Length: 114
Ligand SMILES: COc1ccc(C(=O)NC2CCC2)cc1-c1cc(C(C)=O)n2cccnc12
Ligand code: NA
Ligand code: NA
Image 1 (tube, rainbow, N blue to C red):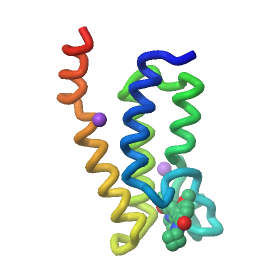
Image 2: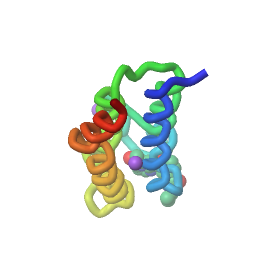
Image 3: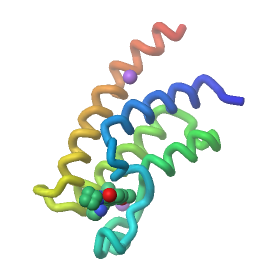
């Protein structure tokens, strides 16, 4: 059993995960691979956690989905230094999400949806 909003969020999540072929954003970061992570980053987030929330119908809106997506990217831009692959990939993914899920793009989706 699924709903229109779950199918829409699954589509955005799939498109964003395509930009992360190696799965750096696929599951939670552990301190063993990222020293000090859990001290620096107080509110972890990852694409696997977001998928689970979609399945449990925990997002009321695209705005709520975007807030978890932005948190994930911000954590990576805060913890990692700028010359690292994780910092650079976080910027690429976040730029893609801004364009995919902007207020303007959603407006048009709604009108067509009416
Ligand atoms: C779930 O997180 C990961 C999973 C797998 C890998 C990984 O396979 N990295 C290889 C490229 C050289 C090792 C890295 C990460 C990873 C993500 C991140 C993030 C998102 O900050 N990170 C930061 C420092 C070190 N490793 C990571
Ligand atoms: Na945080
Ligand atoms: Na799209």
